[PDB]
Structures are given as structure tokens and as C-alpha cells.
């Protein structure tokens, strides 16, 4: 399975800080373990934005039901299914993707 992208944009070198908070406008079911499953209205925190050949996809995690809860797992989803509501930190750190980046969590 080829990497989805060779490079990505993050808020920091380790992609540890979220770039943005977004709300899902469409449902999306993960086609394989690399992807997130999302439903309309759910909140997603975006930690990376892929570049190049993977640029339709962003990486992040789904907010849970209790205040402050964010699932630990990261996965990819199409950027178009969400509306970014708050830019938390500019996503302008241009990083090569590593092998952890497409290994399923």
C-alpha cells in the first residue's frame, strides 16, 4: 500500500498540536483502517493536512460525548466533509511523512 502522501502540513514538527477544530457536514465511513469514520455533526480536531498526491485528505481525531474527550486514534478523512470552525495554530510546518503516519492506530 503506497503512502497516501510524501509530505504533510502540521502546526509543529511533531504534529502534536491541533491545527483546527471542524464540524462534519457529511457522513464518511472509513474504507480501511487508515481512515476515520465520521457522521454529520461530529467534531473533528485536525492535526495534519496531507500534500501532493494525498491533498484531499486531512488527519485527525473525533471528539467524544463528554466535554474534553478526544479519541486517541488518529486517522485520515476527506477535507471536504468538514467545515473548519476555529484555526487553532497555522498549519504551515512542511514535514516529510514517516512510516508511523500510515500505520493503523
Image (cartoon, rainbow, N blue to C red):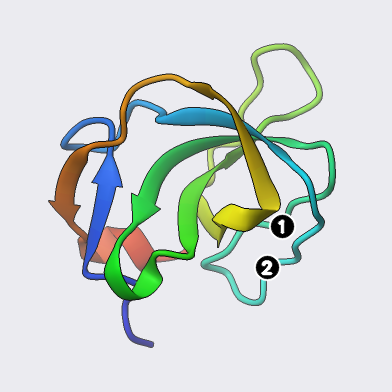
Q: Position of residue 24 (x, y in %)?
A: 74, 43
- Quadrant location of residue 85? top right
- Contact (CB < 8 A) between labels 2 and 1? yes
Residue at 74% in and 51% down: 38
In the picture of the structure, the residue carrying the numbered disc 2 is 30
In the picture of the structure, the residue carrying the numbered disc 1 is 37
- Please report whichever mark, 2 or 1, sits nearer to the chain's N-terminal start: 2
Left or right of 53, for residue 99: left
Q: Is residue 10 above or below residue 89?
A: below
Q: Nearer the viewer, residue 73 or 53?
A: 53
Say what secondary structure mark 1 lies in: loop
Q: Nearer the viewer, residue 90 or 14?
A: 90
Left or right of 60, for residue 53: left
Q: Residues within 10 Å of mark 2 (few under 14, many from 20)?
A: few
Q: Is residue 9 above or below residue 32?
A: above
Residue at 30% in and 62% down: 51
Q: Position of residue 94 (x, y in %)?
A: 16, 47
Can the viewer see residue 55?
A: yes
Residue sticking out furthest to the bottom: 1
Say what secondary structure mark 2 lies in: loop
Inter-mark Cα distance, 2 to 1: 5 Å
Amino acid at each position: 500500500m503506497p503512502k497516501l502522501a510524501d509530505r504533510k502540513l502540521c502546526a509543529d514538527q511533531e504534529c502534536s498540536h491541533p491545527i483546527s477544530m471542524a464540524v462534519a457536514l457529511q457522513d464518511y465511513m472509513a474504507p480501511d483502517c487508515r481512515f476515520l469514520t465520521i457522521h454529520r455533526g461530529q467534531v473533528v480536531y485536525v492535526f495534519s493536512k496531507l500534500k501532493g498526491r494525498g491533498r484531499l485528505f486531512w488527519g485527525g481525531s473525533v471528539q467524544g460525548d463528554y466535554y474534553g474527550d478526544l479519541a486517541a486514534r488518529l486517522g485520515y478523512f476527506p477535507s471536504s466533509i468538514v467545515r473548519e470552525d476555529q484555526t487553532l495554530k497555522p498549519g504551515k510546518v512542511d514535514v516529510k511523512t514517516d512510516k508511523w503516519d500510515f500505520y493503523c492506530q
